[PDB]
Image: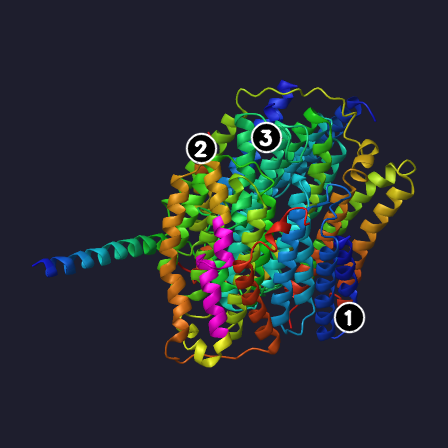
Amino acid sequence: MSYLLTSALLFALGVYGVLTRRTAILVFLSIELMLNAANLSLVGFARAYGLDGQVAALMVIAVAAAEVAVGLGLIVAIFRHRESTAVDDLSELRG
Amino acid sequence: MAPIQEYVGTLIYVGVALFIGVAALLVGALLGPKKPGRAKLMPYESGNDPAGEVKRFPVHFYVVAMLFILFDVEVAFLWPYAVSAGGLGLYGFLGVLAFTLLLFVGFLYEWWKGVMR
Amino acid sequence: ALFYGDRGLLSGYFGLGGAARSLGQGLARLQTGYLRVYALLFVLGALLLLGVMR
Amino acid sequence: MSLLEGLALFLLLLSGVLVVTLRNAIHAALALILNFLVLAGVYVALDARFLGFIQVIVYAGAIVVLFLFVIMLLFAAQGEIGFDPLVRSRPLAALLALGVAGILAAGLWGLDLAFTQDLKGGLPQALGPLLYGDWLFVLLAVGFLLMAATVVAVALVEPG
Amino acid sequence: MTLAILAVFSVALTLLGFVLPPQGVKRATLLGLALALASLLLTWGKPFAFGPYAVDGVSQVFTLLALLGALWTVGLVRSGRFEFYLLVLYAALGMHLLASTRHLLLMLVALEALSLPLYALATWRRGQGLEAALKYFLLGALAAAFFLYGAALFYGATGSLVLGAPGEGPLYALALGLLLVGLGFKAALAPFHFWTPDVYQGSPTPVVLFMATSVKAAAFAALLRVAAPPEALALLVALSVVVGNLAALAQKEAKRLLAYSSIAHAGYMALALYTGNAQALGFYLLTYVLATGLAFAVLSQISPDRVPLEALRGLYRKDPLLGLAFLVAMLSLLGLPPLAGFWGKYLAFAEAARAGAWGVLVLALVTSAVSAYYYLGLGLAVFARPEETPFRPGPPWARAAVVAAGVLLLALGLLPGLVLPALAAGG
């Protein structure tokens, strides 16, 4: 049970990272940490409910890899010619 | 399966290896003249600019690494079929064949487009 | 006098419409355009929902 | 258990704190790799062994390797450039983190579960029939997703 | 066996584009989408399940809507990159998978498969487009993390990852909330709405057409599977509709204003979720998809990058049919009789009142009357004096598409007792 609470804590940590980080890449890293917290909760509940959460987390890892590929390609495309990645540098779109 | 005792032995193995590595680092660091000089600390190649000022490196390495993560996910999925094979029969063979063919079509697209770029 | 009073009543109706518009532009000002701002407001709304669920 | 289990959980939490605190991107990534290692060890302790091994291979071995490749191509290690500091946002972010932890803690509080099932080790020997089978359709969807991700990134960089 | 057609065409064209001109690849994509739609029609009343994949009335109706939106948005795009069609095909298959399953994890995989190609399709390379794509990707990955932890808490509260399981108290409520966060962000409900104005303003107008039709359709299809509590539903609807219409009042740009209007419309559709009738919602979404596709096809004929409000003016004098269809779309999005948008609105409100949510329904109606301000400032502006504005009066392709959309709107507004009888099993 301690594992599920630890996963919730890691989720909160990744949230703090996403909110605090100035860099898009470090935001994405905090998101990956959130994903792995979810995977740990899944593994605990798979130990509880019979191993299906294991295959679940496996598919999750695959999905995470795909989305990491896509998001890093996007990050590179946006900040290859452009200077420092700081996401506050893009404020053109306003209410 | 296998007992956890071998995994504890694995932990022991790692602890022993790390301890030996730290011992080697202590000997190397402690036994030395220790005469720092400005030119000695200077990176390389006669005054400045071994690499000097160069803009961001080619994305070729990024492409290789991303390719690698995707195909490593592929291999990670191929392993459970590699172990549990005879029981999954022609149906499991066909499912894994479909998975492999999808990711190989992705590879063929990225190849006929190529990354020398 | 009653005519002018009716005119002023219609003007107050206009004032109510403008108060609605002002509220709307304050809510549009809520979107500054900074992703950090958008994400903070997002996490805020999500926690609000999870609390309301009880 | 609890002796070394508490140790492993403290290591996980500290690694997360580092990855979200440190302003050096390389240092944060390294903290995250340490996190993934401790997490795979916890996986093994939780009878999920193959999943821990794939967590090391794909996530640590491949994913954050690509991350490191990206941040070494685009230096970015000293992230605090172009600040727009919004100092008021740091305590608000800490507050939102504490709240998202507390609501989950409330949802999981007073919650006890039957953690007694013979997973037999999360070995691929026993995971295969689930993956190819009940999860075969999800597997095929994942593979299609991966192919789509390849084409997406390829057309996404593609200078022309 | 429509998913089979979709996957076959996508995988084949992936390599075929090497030997085929992008025009031929576009023709092929159009043919495949039309063939999948024809199969959906011929399978009307033939629910088909293989794994967690399940085709029922909901799957049929909502995938029909998504296929229509994809066909329309592909018709306009003439770029010589066959990848700009590969991504649309991928997104279509992903939204079909999203609408056709109850498995939470397969739902996540389908979500990623449909969302990733849109991030790339949002790149006309205009500087605002990259900002839009960045906000979209970051907020989307955050919501994916939240949905995944909700699925984990669902697997915690019950032994399966499939919806419909009995469910616990507070923990099940927590899991349901963590799933609802992601689902509403994808449905542009406030207070998760912030991404929508920026993304609609930054993305190319035909892409925004594709989004505002197919994405919203599939999102509400997946929402109907959740057992959303009434208090949470009330909060979402109130905030969404209020903020949407109010902030839309302040908008100077057509795409951003339409984004806020779409936030308000998602707030409206969330009422049918009280009962989850899905016939009312199927009809509502049919009407809304047609109207929005029409409006955005016209906005694409005007300008792909950005269309200001004044650009809409003189549209009648330029093309009378286009001005009239744009007016009809504005009215159907306002939800006024005798239009099918009104019938969808009425069906959603009837589901809500049947659920016994009165104050929420009243607030929704008040905010909908507020929406008439800008709905009329758009529809009626068509008749104003033409100012300096780029205008390319479309091909017969887009002309006939817009006209057929408006005609279907008005016809199903006058006689909804034709199609509405078959949004259930389909007799």
Pointer 2 local density, CA inside 10 Å: few below 14, some 14–19, many at least 20: few
C-alpha separation, residue under disc 3 versus residue under disc 1: 51 Å
Circle 3 is placed at which residue position? D11
| Residue D62 inside the magenta-drawn segment | no
> What is the tally of numbered marks visible in this picture?
3
Q: Chain of mark 1?
A: E
Pointer 1 local density, CA inside 10 Å: few below 14, some 14–19, many at least 20: some
Q: Out of E198 and E302, give the one closest to the viewer.
A: E302
- Is label 3 in a helix, a strand or a loop? helix
Are tags 3 and 1 found on a single chain?
no
Front label number (3 vs 2): 2
> Which SS does the magenta portion mostly show?
helix
Q: Chain of mark 3?
A: D
User: Which residues make up the magenta segment?
Assistant: E322-346
Task: Identify the amino acid type marked 2.
Answer: Gly
- Is label 2 in a helix, a strand or a loop? helix
C-alpha separation, residue under disc 2 versus residue under disc 1: 53 Å
C-alpha separation, residue under disc 3 versus residue under disc 2: 31 Å
Circle 1 is placed at which residue position? E18
Identified at 79% across, 35% down, the residue is: D130
